[PDB]
Image: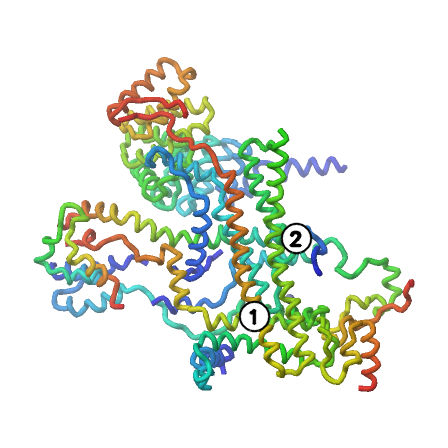
Amino acid sequence: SSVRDVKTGSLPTNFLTGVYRFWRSQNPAEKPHDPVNDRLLPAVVDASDKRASIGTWATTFFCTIISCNLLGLMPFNEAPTSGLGFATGLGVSVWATATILGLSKTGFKFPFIFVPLETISYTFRAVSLGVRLWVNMLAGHTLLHILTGMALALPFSLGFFSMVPATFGVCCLLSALVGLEYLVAVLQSGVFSILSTVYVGEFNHDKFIGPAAKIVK
Amino acid sequence: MKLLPESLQQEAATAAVVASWVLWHLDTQLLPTIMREHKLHACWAAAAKRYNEKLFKLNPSY
Amino acid sequence: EGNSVAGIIKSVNETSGANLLSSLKTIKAQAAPIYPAAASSTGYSTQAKIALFGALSWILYRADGQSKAHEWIVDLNLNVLQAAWLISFSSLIPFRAVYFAFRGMAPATASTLNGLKTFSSISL
Amino acid sequence: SYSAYFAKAGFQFPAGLSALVAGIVALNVCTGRPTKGTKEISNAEYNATPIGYLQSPDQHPTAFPKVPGMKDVHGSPHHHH
Amino acid sequence: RLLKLWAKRLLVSPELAIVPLNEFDAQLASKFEGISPKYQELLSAVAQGNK
Amino acid sequence: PSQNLVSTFANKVIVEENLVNVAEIDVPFWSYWLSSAGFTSKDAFVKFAEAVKPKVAALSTSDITNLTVAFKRANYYDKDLFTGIEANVSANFTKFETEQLLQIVATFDAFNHSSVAFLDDVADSITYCNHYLAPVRAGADELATLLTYYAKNGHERADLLATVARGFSEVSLGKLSAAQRKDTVLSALKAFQTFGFYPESIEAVIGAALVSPAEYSAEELKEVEAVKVAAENALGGEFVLIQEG
Amino acid sequence: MAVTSFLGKAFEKYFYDFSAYEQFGLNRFLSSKGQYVALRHVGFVMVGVNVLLAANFPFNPPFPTIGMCPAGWEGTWVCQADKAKALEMYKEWKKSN
Ligand SMILES: [Zn+2]
């Protein structure tokens, strides 16, 4: 009932400002032909009321996936997006959000032999958006499991703290794969939500209402 | 290895609960705070030329 | 709590000419804003203890089921690989350059405030 | 100057985290199915069976196993093999 | 009353003591953007305090 | 005797005299929701209007909005309550919203009740204490009620009229039915010429009539064309409808 | 002590100015400090691997050995690549040892 107090210019406030303003910049508003003044201001406000909140949705999916992907790089933790229903359940949910937005642009009625081939390549976007997140979080962690088993075979067989140039070259190969996994954790949360702005932004187009009557000169 | 979960609907609903909490938390807690300090700065930087000229025309002190 | 300029105006109006210039540091400090003083510690809040016992209750529970996972020595040697990068990030990230790089992401901190240019609001 | 005002309130959780933790727990306990390695039996079987025979060996793996596949309990020797 | 006038203006806004009283309306113009910038950037930084 | 005990319980416990005895605690909650269910009851609302009068000076702004639109729907006008309501508004005018003031004014416009201090503190609040696009979120049938309430009372606030003229567009009038759009366009042009204020967004309330003139008379289109020529030389040009494309 | 205030100040001066890159000399052998961290990293992994193995050494490995055996075991339960076989041999070995 009493909210907390926030310092202005905090680092999480500055990061989330730049993150939100990034994903909002991916689907920018289009400039009308008219000058924007008090005549055009309800047409601009109504143009914003009909645009989807992709600036908010894409930073919802950025912040929920980069938090899940980076859990996999914390010790004792696995990434939730390394699960099939989690990661592909976010991919179908973006694809259905784009489709529900594109179906409402009409009156919820669904759109010769061409259109089953536009549909297939469009329905594959559903599974491809989630499986790309799932396989990247799975295939990076699986390779790390195999190579840690190989790099444990040498000190198990040879001496503990002995024959160390054999295990140094593979502990530095294991260390450079966890480092690549920090890059794939940040990239795949970016690629998921760059693509969410692209798919949802396809149906983010409505008619500018504008002035129907003018007093020229 | 582990490919399919024990329930796919339980993992899909965990994703929808996590991503709808992040949607609620952003819309309700983060973005009001973002915009309170983004738009104090932005309104002051956009009005600064017309605020000061309106105030120059108003105060009789010159 | 009325505003401090009307407290300045009242406190300067009801002083005399003789003690005007002596009173100006106690009218200055009566209208200074409150910056609350650094209280005693009372450290580790009732929620900072939930956050650290609940994180220890999570790390012990995750290390418990990692140790019986059929690849248990590979699972427990991945926490060594993952915590090696948490150590190398404390020693490689420029934390002052990162702090001032996030300050530029936000337009509120990327500049200075800009209104009210002092020659418009004089009272002569 | 305001630095000591922000040190007073210490740690605090995010402002609705009790609804995230109660939502993730309510998905993991309201599964609507038995609890992952168990099977619902009748009350006549549960009252008649020892607690060493209700346990399966697969559900109690050894906490740091010297051989991969060691289990802590052994369960019912009355197999239907 | 002149001493009490300037007491309030220098308790609230003490940076005003850096534009001398004779050189004040030599700064003005008809528009606010035309005011001479001799003291503008100095007044803005003295107003931000001693740190 | 089961039917006898229920019927005896129904004639002495559940009546409207005890329905107004539980409704004495919080008045503007129970006043607002009952009147939305269709409970007018003119002399049950007099029990409301005296139970709330020691509280009107300390109500929140959403409580004051709930009193006036309930006492509008029940059509009951208590003049010494409605001066305590306008003394809540004109004492807390910075806290009211345009969503709340446009519903309080439309109550005060039905019951022809105004003050000069109230008409300034509603216009000061819509213009300065509220967001400048709050008229755009209003719906033009409520803004025309505010425009005539300032023309009935002869109150010329040229700053308020530039604010309310934002909320007239093709968007805001297109959400109206053409029976209600006609009742608004004539009501807005009658107020725009009473002050002689012809903003650049008068060409959307004029063009809402001239794009469909078959709903208007020739007497009302003479009223419309009187404002069109009055606005054409003020804005410095000539009116022209646009065929889209 | 105050439990949050002592070792926070001890960890602070272990984190910041406690530096074995200069207190142990070590600029004689290493070029930068960016490559002292890049092998303190790999040194942390090799130490942590060798501690995790040695803290329970007589174990049949879950990971595939590449055809190698630790010490004088070579036919025991530790090197047996069939796991139900080695469970039988470990239970025999545990009575003796
Ligand atoms: Zn793992």
Same subunit, tags 2 and 1: yes
Residue drawn at x 57%, y 43% as measured from the top left? A97
| Residue tagged 2 | A85
In the picture, the quarter occupied by the C terminus of chain C is bottom left
Protein chain holding label 1: A
* Residue A169 x %, y %: 58, 74
Q: Quarter of the image containing the N terminus of chain C?
A: bottom left
| For residue F201, above or below residue C33 | above
Q: Chain of mark 2?
A: A
The part of the image, by quadrant, that contains residue D29 is bottom right
Mark 2–mark 1 Cα distance, whole angstroms, equals 29 Å
Q: Is residue B49 visible?
A: yes
| Residue drawn at point x = 16 percent, y = 58 percent | E39
Mark 2 CB lies closer than 8 A to ligand 1: no
Foreground of the two, A96 or F181 = A96
In this orientation, which residue lies closer to the viewer: A53 or F164? A53
* Amino acid at pointer 2: Gly
Question: Does residue D64 appear left or right of residue F35 in this picture?
Answer: right
Along the horizontal axis of the image, is F89 left or right of F177? Answer: left
Q: Is residue F2 left or right of residue F207?
A: right
